[PDB]
Amino acid sequence: AKGSVLVTDAEGQPVADATVEFKVYNYAEFYTVATKHTDRSGHASLTAGKGDMLVWASKDGRFGYSKLSFGKDNELKITLDK
Image (cartoon, rainbow, N blue to C red; front, side, top):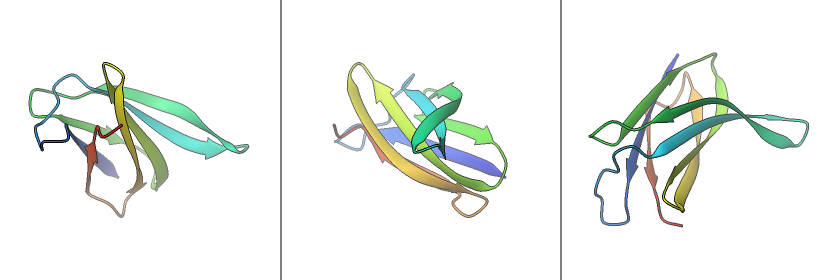
């Protein structure tokens, strides 16, 4: 299915051109399978096999992450809160 990501800063503002890595868990670690950059609205999308991915969003050393269940979750909002 399709998995969409919204990346915002701590003040709810969309982050343009944040790096968005989608990772799959294997052998006790997460392996990046795709790398996207958010558009001017703070959105990035991936089409992939149904399944759980860790989504890792970063911009200039600020970062946030969450699980996206592809085929169950439609759009994940990630707060670059770290």
